[PDB]
């Protein structure tokens, strides 16, 4: 993807931080799933 | 407490008497079959028989027949 961003001529640092924020996006979506499962009890839940 | 919330108390309160005497539990037992009728032994006897559900906290009633601490009891 670094070289792909270079093929797209934009600097790969921008694509790298886009990628990292995308990781953060699905991570927050997974936190949302944690809230779909436990709601808010996951702050004290064992697995939570 | 619940199975996992060790920070949030499920039902935490007290069972204190009217005056300033420090209520010292002595081998207190849970209600037999969770009928809420639990007993609390004390050092001068002082069987604190009380209920759990509703507004029946604190000290419901008591009875003494001796002055020793009840270190063994069994609600049955």
Image: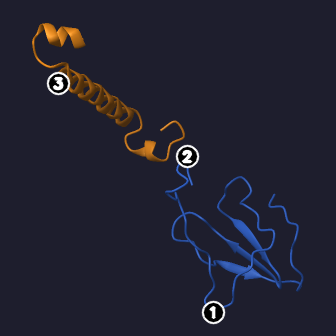
Q: Position of residue B34 (x, y in %)?
A: 67, 55
- Structural crowding at the residue carrying mark 3, measured as other residues with C-alpha within 10 Å and reported as few (<14), some (14–19) or many (≥20): few
Q: Which residue is mark 3?
A: A14
Do the residues under discs 2 and 3 have CB atoms within 8 angstroms? no
Q: In the shown orientation, is residue A29 left or right of residue B73?
A: left
Q: In the shown orientation, is residue B34 left or right of residue B66?
A: left
Residue at 74 percent of width and 79 percent of height: B24
> How is the structure coloured here?
by chain
Do the residues under discs 1 and 2 have CB atoms within 8 angstroms? no
C-alpha separation, residue under disc 1 versus residue under disc 2: 36 Å
Find numbered disc 2 in the image and state the secondary structure of the residue it sits on.
loop
Chain letter of the residue carrying label 3: A
- Structural crowding at the residue carrying mark 2, measured as other residues with C-alpha within 10 Å and reported as few (<14), some (14–19) or many (≥20): some
**Nearer the observer, disc 2 or disc 3?**
3
Q: Which mark is residue B19?
A: 1
Q: Which residue is mark 2?
A: B4
């Amino acid at each position: 993807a670094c070289k792909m961003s270079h093929v797209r001529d934009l600097p790969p640092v921008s694509g790298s931080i886009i990628w990292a924020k995308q990781i953060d996006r699905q991570l927050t979506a997974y936190m949302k799933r944690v809230e779909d499962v436990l709601g808010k009890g996951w702050e004290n839940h064992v697995e939570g | 407490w619940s199975l996992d919330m060790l920070s949030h108390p499920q039902d935490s309160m007290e069972l204190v008497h009217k005056q300033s005497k420090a209520v010292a539990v002595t081998s207190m037992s849970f209600p037999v079959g969770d009928v809420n009728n639990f007993v609390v032994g004390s050092e001068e006897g002082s069987v604190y028989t009380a209920c759990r559900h509703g507004s029946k906290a604190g000290i419901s009633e008591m009875f003494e027949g001796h002055q020793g601490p009840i270190t063994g009891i069994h609600c049955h």
